[PDB]
Image (tube, rainbow, N blue to C red; front, side):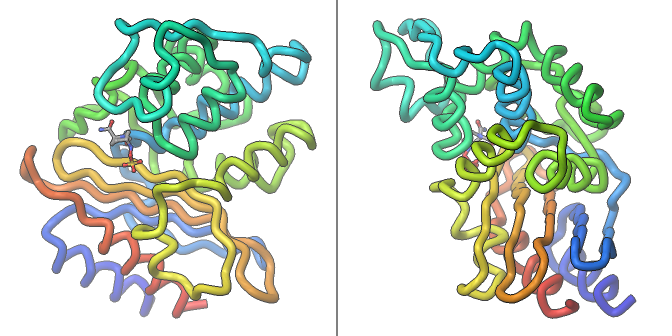
Amino acid sequence: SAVQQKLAALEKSSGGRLGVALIDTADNTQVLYRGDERFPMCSTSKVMAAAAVLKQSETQKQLLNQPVEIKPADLVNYNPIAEKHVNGTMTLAELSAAALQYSDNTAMNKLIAQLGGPGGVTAFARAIGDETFRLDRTEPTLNTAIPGDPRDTTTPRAMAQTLRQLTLGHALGETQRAQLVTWLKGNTTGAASIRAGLPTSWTVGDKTGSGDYGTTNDIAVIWPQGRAPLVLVTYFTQPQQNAESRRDVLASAARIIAEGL
Ligand SMILES: *C(=O)N1C[C@H](NOS(=O)(=O)O)CC[C@H]1C(N)=O
């Protein structure tokens, strides 16, 4: 299609590998580009981990308010919130917000630990019907983004379907879905990514990610003015291990998608 032409040209100009999956919930139409190829999720995997803890809280009713110890040795490579609470505690709700809205990697490791390790995140994915997602490692090694390595990857098609079920469908209970959407809408890291390619009047909740090989990712739920929501995944990775981030490529992909509606 014409959108296919434009996405391919954007990819060729970028020098990297671009993966796009859109679901338009107005009519269940889709736009897919490399939609069945695996890409390293990096920090976008935090959505699955926070959602899995939310699901646990449906039956452990006070789980989100349980204190979790933060030790100096727990700090990893990017810990803007957890570093303020070392030698103290944060609750699982606070850790979820830190992971999602500030992309705190120590907070993500606490979510993973609550779930019993990376396999617990994968098990939640399987429980909600996602047979493609896999989490294999903790932070920071889940971000190595090595070409051909299936660890810590998913496909754009699978992640868009799962993000729709989590934020607009019934994979979570009503209050928990609302909490996840509230957290995504309050993200601090997203203005240069999918959001930058969309009309300013549209409402976006998103989670970004980045890693080695210049990996630059964003996954979003979008409420355009006057119409039903969209779900958009944009994943991007590059040939050189030390490549620079390319958030502009994600914005350009979203802009192409928004024009083609
Ligand atoms: C997640 O991809 N990471 C944690 C933090 N995320 O910030 S981003 O979502 O704005 O990219 C830093 C980058 C990355 C990592 N390598 O840990």
